[PDB]
Image (cartoon, rainbow over all chains, first blue to last red; front, side, top):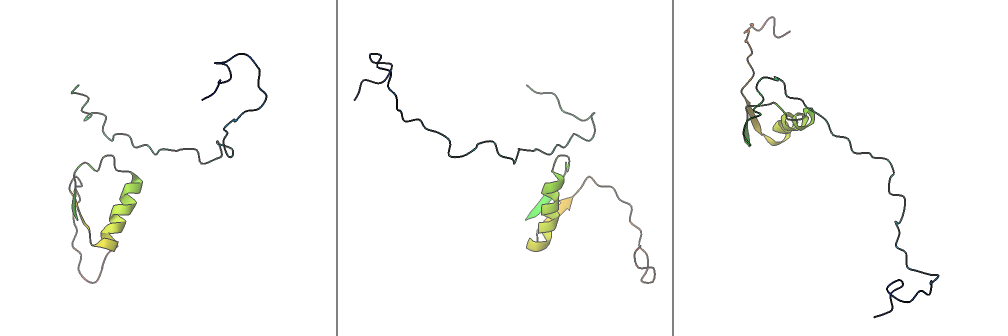
Length: 49
Length: 49
């Protein structure tokens, strides 16, 4: 076990293990859902709960 | 599968391409019931139009 920068002294250390994303994360292929609307707006349960 | 279809409400245009499409390829039988269609019966001379 070790100090733990922060939970220990103050020696600002200058080198860490930063974990990062391997490559851009927001590249195209934006989700897209198809929508079907009820076809009667008069036979729409609504009841229960 | 003998698949029975009663609402035929939601069911994406896409889910349908596939079932009708697979009735074919896999001998599936879909049984559709909220349709209402008259039914002419022309003789082998004016065969379909």
